[PDB]
Amino acid sequence: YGYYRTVIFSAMFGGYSLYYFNRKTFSFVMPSLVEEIPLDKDDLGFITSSQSAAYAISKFVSGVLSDQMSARWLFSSGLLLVGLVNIFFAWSSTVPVFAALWFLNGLAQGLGWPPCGKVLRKWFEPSQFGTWWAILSTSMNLAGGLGPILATILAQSYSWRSTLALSGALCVVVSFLCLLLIHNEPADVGLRNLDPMEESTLQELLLSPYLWVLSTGYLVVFGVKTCCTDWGQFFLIQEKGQSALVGSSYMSALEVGGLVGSIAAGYLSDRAMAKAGLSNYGNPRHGLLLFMMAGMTVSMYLFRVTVTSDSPKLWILVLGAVFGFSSYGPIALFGVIANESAPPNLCGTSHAIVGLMANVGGFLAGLPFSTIAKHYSWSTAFWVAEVICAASTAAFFLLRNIRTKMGRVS
Ligand SMILES: O=P(O)(O)OC[C@H]1O[C@@H](O)[C@H](O)[C@@H](O)[C@@H]1O
Image (cartoon, rainbow, N blue to C red; front, side):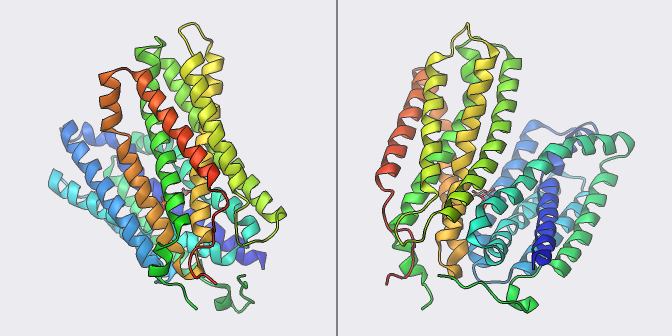
């Protein structure tokens, strides 16, 4: 019975890794193109913006669609389309064709997660859902970590035209293999399907306060994380008077702390869920959620106040790691909670809505924050961000007891 789980999880891991690698291959192979074709910065910004917009639309559309359609076919079709786009990218010469192909790639990138989430929910009991979710989500981290080395090594021996086509062909072959391997439901194999604890309707799903509470929480958390990640180096350089290498080390520490935080949050949340009992109200992951948001606020306060022009690098690295931990925990916890608590027949819609709120929150922490910083100072902007985070965490603590199982009310 575990052999099927092992095979399915390995197939999903490989598929998602190839997804992310061929999403980032363009930035990986930037040089050979820039010294092959005289491209300007505006054109590259245009291409990246087109891909980002296509992916942002395709995430919501793919979630809503995968709420209904099968998982194996959708996953394989997405991977095949991405591979074909990467193949066609190797013969392109003019910028408009580059932009059109990359927009198509961004559209096809949306069919990556929702099938994996649906299969993971259908095949795994709730006591391991969060742990295996985090383990699967580390695949994109691995691909990003091991991309540039391979890209540079291959470019040192061959041009990009021989680099993108090979990856596209690999995508096609792996897509066919994953179509062969992945099984959507245990009953298809011929086993005993899991029994969950009157189909729900979107009308009676949208009228649940817990969904809006979760959406607001994710908006706030994602906005704060994006703001800190964007402007930490500038805050450390312009006023604190440090060096650039300190900023680079602080970024690396934040990334490592974030990875560790995501994995630890998943593991501890799964352990607490398994140990605790069953009830309609509340959710066992709320304790870890609130603890990590408290870590958010405390780390922000200490970084804003204590760090001065005469502080050792060790303090800065420790603060960065702690903030990364406490900021990459709740981001995964919101996704796990949003997928799990939803009724089985509407698992993707909640995740899609939460992601759209995440997009709005990520927008909110862009130009307005820079405007505020350039108006008064950087410290004032970080102070208002900290106040927002503290108010949000207090409000979320007050509403820990509201009904969680959204959908049909009996
Ligand atoms: O593409 P999506 O829908 O945003 O999924 C990716 C991320 O979505 C978040 O909701 C999850 O918490 C993360 O674990 C996951 O990595």
